Image: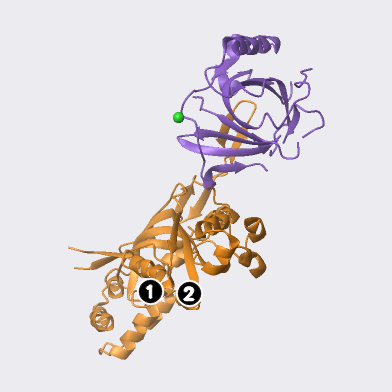
Chain colours: A orange, B purple
Amino acid sequence: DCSQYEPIPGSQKAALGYNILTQEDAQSVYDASYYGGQCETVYNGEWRELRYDSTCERLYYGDDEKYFRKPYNFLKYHFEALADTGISSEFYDNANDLLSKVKKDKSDSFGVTIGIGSPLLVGVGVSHSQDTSFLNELNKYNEKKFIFTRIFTKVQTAHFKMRKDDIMLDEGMLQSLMELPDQYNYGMYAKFINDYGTHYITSGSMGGIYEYILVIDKAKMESLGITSRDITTCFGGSLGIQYDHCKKFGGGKTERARKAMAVEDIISRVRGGSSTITYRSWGRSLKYNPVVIDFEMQPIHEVLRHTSLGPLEAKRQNLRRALDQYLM
Amino acid sequence: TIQPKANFDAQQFAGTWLLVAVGSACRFLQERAEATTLHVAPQGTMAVSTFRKLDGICWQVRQLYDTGVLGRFLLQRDARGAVHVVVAETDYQSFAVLYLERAGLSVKLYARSLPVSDSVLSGFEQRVQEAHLTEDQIFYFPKYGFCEAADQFHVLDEV
Ligand SMILES: [Cl-]
């Protein structure tokens, strides 16, 4: 049959709605598992075992090229060539200046065009969580006593497009939709928006973000005769990133180890893939487990214009009306 | 049959070598060569990184070279034949002649810098003739377009 192939990586994630107010995912909008009688597959010749014959100086390819099954709601999916995009290092004197560059990057995070008339919202570097953990972790360390470093990178594994018409919605969403009243009711419609999102993905990119923040006891660091860059470079090296106390730091697996380099906390913000994880181990794990790192999206009510249930139009105008109020 | 350099010093052999030429009855080589660099470190007493392109992209190959003579090494793979590497002649500081024997052999000339001297080159051609290879079967590798690094997705790590 056709079921022997793994699905296109990330297909379950691209199927989810998005809430722009909460900046988190909602339940599935698209049916991610629907194939509809058709066996479409995608060749991946970006992740094969290279061979090297040292005797003849021959660096050649393994015939271990894979096929992935593309579900009906994905019009296209293209695996990218994996590449290191450059690893950034930043240093901050205080939590706020880090928080600031972070939230500023949440304004770098979103663009917009308007169809010829639906908004098309454009998330770039999108994390799919409220960062409530991260914000509360960091707020433990908003004191003059602490300084911060941050390494960040981003990799895309694929670009995809969703289908534009005869969309098959998730059984969950369909049932919810059936249950919405024809008579406008903000409560019922807001609930639906809370369950399925303010927006759904029409295209995007799979991949990940590899990112760590270090919190550092400045006073302790000085005493050790080291610097914030020393610490970061040592931490970097522990992650496999190519460039006494450091040796003692190791991977910073213990608090003992971390305190050898004045490191109070290692805060992870890694997304996609998978203590800490090594750069190369993270890169591997992005083959099979990406997130939708960048995407285009449209208002939830737009999808009702393009489903296989056909004309669905007073629920659509109620949903739009409701979304107008919800977004304010 | 081929003897390793007497008293081969892995420590002085360490560092970066440029592939200059290979003598070989390899079917592959007789039918686009890439600039190839070797990075050598003794590990115990040798870790060997080869950098070179494939279809415009830089790769790092990691291997290990450890049997108990000096300039004789065992390279292991998948269902490949094991390869014996012999560092037959080198001055540590300008050139090196390595022999690789699978089953029934290639002779490689490396240098620390280019150009190689006339005498290093003649001596290599003489060895190739003595390995029952013709001048036809000497393939010279490029002198530019070296890979200074490979990213983490383009490391083929056999270690
Ligand atoms: Cl060059």
Residue at 80% x, 33% y is B67
**x and y percentages locating residue A227 in the rendered image:** 52, 59
Q: Secondary structure at mark 1?
A: loop
Which residue is situated farthest in the left direction here?
Answer: A116
The residue mark sitting in front, 1 or 2, is 2
Residue at 76% x, 18% y is B2
Q: Residues within 10 Å of mark 2 (few under 14, many from 20)?
A: many
**x and y percentages locating residue A47 in the rendered image:** 53, 47
Q: Residues within 10 Å of mark 1 (few under 14, many from 20)?
A: some
**x and y percentages locating residue A13 in the rendered image:** 45, 66
Report whether residue A5 is seen: no
Which image quarter is the C terminus of chain B in?
A: top right
Q: Amino acid at mark 1?
A: Gln
Q: Amino acid at mark 2?
A: Leu
- Using the image as rendered, state which of residue A203 and residue A4 is in the foreground: A203
Q: Secondary structure at mark 2?
A: helix
On the same chain: label 1 and label 2? yes
- Residue at image mark 2: A138
Residue at 37% x, 66% y is A101
**Image: A83 above or below A25:** above
Distance between the alpha carbons at the discs numbered 1 and 2: 19 Å
Q: Chain of mark 2?
A: A
- Residue at image mark 1: A23
From the viewer's perspective, tell me whether residue B136 is left or right of residue A204: right
Label located before the other in sequence (1 or 2): 1
From the viewer's perspective, tell me whether residue A30 is left or right of residue A119: right
Determine the image quadrant of residue A49: top right
